[PDB]
Image: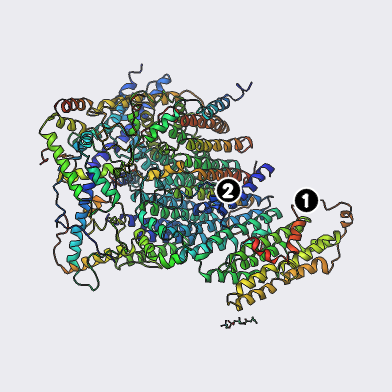
Amino acid sequence: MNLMITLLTNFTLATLLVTIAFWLPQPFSMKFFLVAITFLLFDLEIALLLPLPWASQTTNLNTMLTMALLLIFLLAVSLAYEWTQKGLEW
Amino acid sequence: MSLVYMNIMMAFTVSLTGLLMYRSHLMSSLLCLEGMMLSLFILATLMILNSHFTLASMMPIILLVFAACEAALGLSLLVMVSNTYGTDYVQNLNLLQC
Amino acid sequence: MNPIILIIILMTVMLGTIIVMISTHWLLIWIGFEMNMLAIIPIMMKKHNPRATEASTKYFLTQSTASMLLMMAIIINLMFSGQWTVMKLFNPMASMLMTMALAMKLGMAPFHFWVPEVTQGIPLSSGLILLTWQKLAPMSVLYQILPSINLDLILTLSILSITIGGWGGLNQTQLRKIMAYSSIAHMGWMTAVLLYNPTMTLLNLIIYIIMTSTMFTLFMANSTTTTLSLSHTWNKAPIMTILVLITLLSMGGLPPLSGFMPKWMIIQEMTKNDSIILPTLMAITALLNLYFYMRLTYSTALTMFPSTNNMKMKWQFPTTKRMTLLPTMTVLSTMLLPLTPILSILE
Amino acid sequence: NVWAKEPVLVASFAIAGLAVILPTLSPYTKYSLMINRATPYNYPVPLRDDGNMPDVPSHPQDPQGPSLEWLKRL
Amino acid sequence: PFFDVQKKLGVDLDHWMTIQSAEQPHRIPARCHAFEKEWIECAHGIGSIRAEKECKIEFEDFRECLLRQKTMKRLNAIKRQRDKLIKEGKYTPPPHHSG
Amino acid sequence: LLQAEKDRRVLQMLRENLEEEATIMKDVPGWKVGESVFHTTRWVTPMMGELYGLRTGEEILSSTYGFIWYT
Amino acid sequence: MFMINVLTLIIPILLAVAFLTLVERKVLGYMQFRKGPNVVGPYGLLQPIADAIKLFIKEPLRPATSSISMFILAPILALTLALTMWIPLPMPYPLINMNLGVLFMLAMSSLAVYSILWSGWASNSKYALIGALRAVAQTISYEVTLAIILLSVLLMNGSFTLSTLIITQEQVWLIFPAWPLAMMWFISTLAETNRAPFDLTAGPFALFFMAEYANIIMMNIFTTTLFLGAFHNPYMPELYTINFTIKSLLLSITFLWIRASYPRFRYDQLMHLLWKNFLPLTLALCMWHVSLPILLSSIPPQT
Amino acid sequence: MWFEVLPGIAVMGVCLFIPGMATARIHRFSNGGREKRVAHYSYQWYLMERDRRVSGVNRYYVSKGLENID
Amino acid sequence: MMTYIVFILSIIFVMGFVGFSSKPSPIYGGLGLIVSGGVGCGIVLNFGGSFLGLMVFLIYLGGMMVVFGYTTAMATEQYPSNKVVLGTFITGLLMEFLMVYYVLKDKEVEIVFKFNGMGDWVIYDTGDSGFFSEEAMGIAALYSYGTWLVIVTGWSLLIGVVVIMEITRGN
Amino acid sequence: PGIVELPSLEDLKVQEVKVSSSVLKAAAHHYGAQCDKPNKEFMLCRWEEKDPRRCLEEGKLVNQCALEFFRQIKRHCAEPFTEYWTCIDYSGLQLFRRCRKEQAQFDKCVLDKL
C-alpha cells in the first residue's frame, strides 16, 4: 500500500495540475503496419529470453547455453528472413 | 474456495459474451478476446501462485506469448479486410452467402 | 507462394498434429491446436480474392474462441483436482466446456455455421488439408478424454449433427458445400460411437479421410465447382465418370462397396448395447444424406447433359494434371468389403 | 572484399562465431560447474548414523567429507 | 491415439511438467505434496474405475487439501456465530492481543 | 532455532484458538470441538486463518500481507 | 514522514525541470555565440519561473476537437509517469525497494508510447494523425534494443534489484567491460528522449513539456547509476550523492552538447540504420555477454 | 565566458542534490542511526518479524542488546 | 480501504471488463482494457506476486494494446450515446451489486459450486523459509528443464513471423 | 473424522532466547560450530517424523544449548563482541564483508581466551 499511496498522491497532484490549468483560466500505408507486428514478435522472443539471469545458477549449464544461443540464433534467422525477403524495405 | 476465483470466472463469461455479441466493429470483438485472454491469465496465475505449484509455472508466460501472437494474426487479418474493402464492419460481408 | 515456405508450413501442420497426438500434458495440446491453426491459415488465401479473406477470417475467429474455451476447461480442471495428466477429468462443467470446445473445433450442428462458408471460397488444396487434418487432430484428444464425458452432450451433438448435415445440401449446387455437409454428418457418426468403443471411431476416421482424399483428388483432376462442369468431364473423359459413380456410392454407404463397413460395424458395437431406436434413427438419416449424392450421380454419369464446344479443342490435349495418389486410395476405398476382420488392424 | 561493403555485419558474424565456438577450449567450465554445485540452498539433513558407512562425518571439523580448498585458491 | 513415443524413445521430455513431487530444481514442496504422493500410491496399478471405487477417501482428503472447502465452511460458520453472539453482546473480547 | 520457535508458537496459537473454539460453541447441534474435516490423521499446515483468525483485522493484516508490500 | 518523503521527491521536479530548461537554453547559447537569458533579472531563473507561470495561465487551447475525456486522459498519464518514475531509482537509499525495477522502467516507457498514441488519436485531422503515427513507430522501434541491452548488462550482475548493481560498481566502472553496449544504449536513450537528431515537424504543452523533460532527467539518472558511478560508503551518503549529481550533470551537458551539433536523419534511413546496424550488433554483443560469464567462472551472486 | 551558465547549473544541481539527501536524512532519523532493513526474501522477513516480536514496542530498531540472556 | 482489498480490486477488474464489453468505440475499449490489465497486475502482485504481473504489463500493456490503438488509428474511422451500450453498463453495475449483495448480507454465493464467501487472505503461506522467491526459481526452471518447450515455442514464433509477412504480402 | 492431538499449555512453556536477530546472525559461525551438535537429533526427528506435536523435547534441548552458549559468550571475552554486532547492525542487512576489523578482533579474542 506504500507504493499505491505514492501513486495515488502523484495522480492527485497531477489532476490538481490539470484543474488549475483548465478551470482556473476561465487512409494509411501497409508498409507502416509491418513495424508493429515485427516489433511484437521480436518483443515476444524478448519475453522468452529475459528470465535468463534467474536460471544462471542451476546444475544444468550446457543445455541452457545451447538452447539460449539457439533462441537468439532463431531470432536472427527471422531477422535475416525479413531482411532478405523485402519485409523491411522502402 | 477463494471467492475472487468466482469473480474472475464471471469476468471471463462477461468477456465471452462481449466476444460473441458485437454489432459493427470487429476490433471490439478481438479486443474482448484479448480481455478474455487476460482473464484466463489472471485466474491460472493466482491458482498456481497460491497453491505453491512452483515447478510448472510456465503456464502464465506461455499462454501469454501464444495467445498474444494469435491476437497479432487477427489484427493482420483485420487489416487485410479493411484494405480490400471500405470499412471493417460485420456489414459488407453479405457476399459468400450460405 | 514459395515452395520452401510451403514445405515449412506442411512441416508445421505435421508437427502440430503430432504434438497433439503425443503429449501427456494439456499445455502442449493447446499449443498444438494453436500451431495447427497458425499453419492452416496461410494455405488458405492462396489467391487474394476477398472470398478467401472472409472465409479465413470466419475460420480464424471460430478457431481462436475454441482454443480459448479449451484453455478455460483446463484451468477449471486445475481449479478442481489439479494435475497435468491428459486423462479422465473431474467436473461435469469442465467436461461440458471441453466437449463444446472440441465441437466448435471439428464441427457439430450447433456449431456448423462456419464450415460451408469456409470451404466455399477457398481453393481445393486448402480444403483438402483442412478437412483431413482438422477432422483428424481432435479425435486423438477425444480418445484420451473418453472416460469422463456426460453422454447427453455427445449424443445430442451427434444426433443433431447427422440430421442437420443430412438436411443441408438439398438446395446447394456447390460441390464444396456438398462435401462440407457430408463431413459434418460423418463427424456426427464418428463421434456417436465414442463412449462404447473408440476403435470404430478411429477406424471410421481413417476410412472417411481416405474417402475425402479420393473425392478431392477426383476434383483436382478437373477444375470444377458446379455439376455442369461434371457433365463436361463426362463428355471429355470416360474414367472420371465411373470413378465419381463408385466413390459417391461409397460415400452413400451401400453394402457391396466399402462405405458400408463403417456403418455396419457401428451398428454391431452400438446395438450390442440395447440402444436400438437410436441406431435405426441414425441409419434412417444415413438413408437421408444420400439424395444429393444421387442427384449428383445423375448429373455426372447416369443422365447426360448437352455440352458446349471447345471441348473439341480440349480433346487434343491430355488431362495433364498431377495426382498425389489417386488409384491406390481409390481401390483401398472401394473394394475393402471382405476385410472386415481387419477392423482390428487399428486395435 | 566485403570488409567495406557492410562492415558491421562482418564484425557481427565474427564475434557471433567466436561466441559459438569458444566454449570448446577454455579451462573454466568445470570450475563453473563446481562453483554452482558447491552452493547449498537446501538444508543438509543429518541421517541415521550407520549402515556401516565409512564416510558421512559426524563432526563438520573432520575433513573426511566432500571437502573444498580450491574455493579459497582461485 | 495416445501414442507413447514419450516412453518408446527412452526420452522423458514432458513428464517434469506434469504433477508435483518431481524434483524442482531448488527442492521445495508445495502445500499438498504428501496428499499427491499418497493418492498416487493408492491408485497406481489400478484400472482407473476401481480407483474411483476404492481410492475415494484419500482423493477427498487431497481435494480438501487443495481447495479447503469444508474447512472454510466451518471457519465461516464460527465467524458468523461469533458475529451474532457479540452483536447480542457477550464477552467484550479478550481473544485479541492476549488470552 | 528459528524452526523450533516457529513450531512452538504455532502450536501455541492452535491451543489458544481451539480453547476459544471450545468456549464459543456450546449452542449448535453437532459440533465436536476439534474434529478436523481431514479423514486421514497427519499433521497439516494451517491455512493462516486457523492461526490468525478472530484477531479483528489489524494484527492479521500486519502478519499476513506484511512482506507483500513492506516497501 | 512517508508523505514527507513523497513531497520532498516530487516538489523539486518543478524546480529541476524549469532550471534544466534554463541550463539547456544557456548551453545552446554558448555553443552558439550568445548570452541569455540573463537580462531579465539575475541570470535568468526568475525567467523560467515567469514563463512557466505564463504558460500555465495562458488561455486553454480550446477544442476545436472532440473527446474531452481522452484529451484529459492522455497528459494525465504522461505526467503521472513523470512523477512515478523517479521512485525506485536508487540514489543510495531509494524510496521503494523492489525485487525488480528495470522491467518496470521498460513498462513505463511503453506507457509513454500509449500517451503519444492517445494524444495522436484525439488530436486533429488526418495529417496530425499520420505524423503522430510515424512518431509512435519511431518511438516503439527502440524498446527492442534498449530492453535487450539492459538485459545483457544486468546479466553481468544477476539481480534485477539494481542495488546489487550499485554494489558491483565499486571496483571498476561498468563502462570498461561494456563500452560498445553502453554506447548503443546511450544512443537508444537519445532516441527515446525524441530530441535532436530526431523530429517533431497541440496542448497541453505544459504537461507534455514536463513529461519529456522529466523523462530526460530520469534517463540521465538511470544512466549515471547504470553504467558508471563510484563506491557508496554508509554513514556518509552525501559524498556519494554529490559525486552522483556531478556525474549526472556532466552527462546531461554531454547530451545537450551532442544535441547542438548534427542535422536530422531520414526516416527510411532511420529504420535502415536501426535494424541493419543495431540489431545484429546488439544480438552479437548479447550472445557474447551470455557465453562469456559461463566461461570465466563468474556467474553472479543473484541470491 | 561560461561563468554565467554555472549558477544556473549550480541551483539546478542543488535541486538534484536535495531529494536523496533529505530522503537519507529521514531514513536515518526514522530508524535511530540505522539503515532500514531491506526486505527482499521471506526468510529475512521472518527474521525481521521475530525481531519486532522480541522488541515488545511493536517496532524493530530497538534490538534488545544482550541484557536479557537470563 | 479495508481487509477485502483483493476483492475490491477484483470488483474494479470486473468493472473494467464490463466497461469494454459494452462495445464502445475501440480506443475507449482499449482504455478500458488497459485499466483492466493494470488492476489485474495489482491483484496478482497482491497475492505475491513477484514477477508475473509485471511481466504481462510489458506484454499486453506494453506491446498489444499499442497494436490495438495502432490498428484503431490506421483502419477504423468514426466519422460523423447509444442506449444499448449504456443499458448494458447499467446491467453490469447492477449484477455486480447483486453478487456483492449476496456475498455481504448473506453467507455465500453458489451458481453451480460452493464458493465460501469471505475474505481471501486465506489461503496463504505461514511464512516459510523461502529465501529465493519461489516464482523466480520457478521461471528459472523453464531453462533448466525446458528442452522441448522452448523449441516448440520459438518455432511457433518463427512461423508467426513468416505467416504474418506472407499474409501481408510475402515477400 | 479424526480428533486433534495437540500438546496442551503444560508443554507450551520453555523459556526462549530473548535476543535480537542482529546479534543472532552476528554470532552465526561460533553458534553453529561449538553448539548445534545435538540439534541434529532434532533435525533428524523432524525429517523422519514430519510431526510437530512429537519432536518438541529436542527443541527444548536446542533452546537450552543456546542458553548455555550465550552464557559462555556473555561472562567471558568479548564485551567488544557487543561492539561487533552494533557495528554490523546499522549496515543494512548484515553483510559479513562490512565490519571486518572488529570481526578479526573478536576472532583473536575468542581464540586466545576461549
* In the depicted structure, whether residue G237 falls above or below residue A19: above
Within 10 Å of disc 2 (Cα), the crowding (few <14, some 14-19, many 20+) is some
Question: Secondary structure under badge 1?
Answer: loop
Residue, disc 2:
B76
Residue J56, label in figure? none
- Give the SS element for disc 2: helix
| Quadrant housing residue A79 | top right
Q: Amino acid at mark 2?
A: Ser
- In the rendering, at what x and y percent does residue D51 appear? 32, 44
Q: Which residue is mark 1?
A: C322
Q: Are marks 2 and 1 on the same chain?
A: no
Measured as percent of width and height from the top left, residue I37 is found at: 42, 50
Q: CA distance from mark 2 to mark 1?
A: 34 Å
How many residues crowd around disc 1 within 10 Å: few (fewer than 14), some, or many (20 or more)?
A: few
* Chain ID at mark 1: C
Q: Chain of mark 2?
A: B
Q: What is the quadrant of the C terminus of chain B in the image? A: bottom right
Q: Is residue A87 above or below residue E45?
A: above
Q: Return the residue nearer the eye: I79 or C28.
A: C28
**What sort of colour scheme is used for the picture?**
rainbow
Q: Position of residue B14 (x, y in %)?
A: 45, 61
- Give G31 or C6, whichever is nearer the viewer: C6
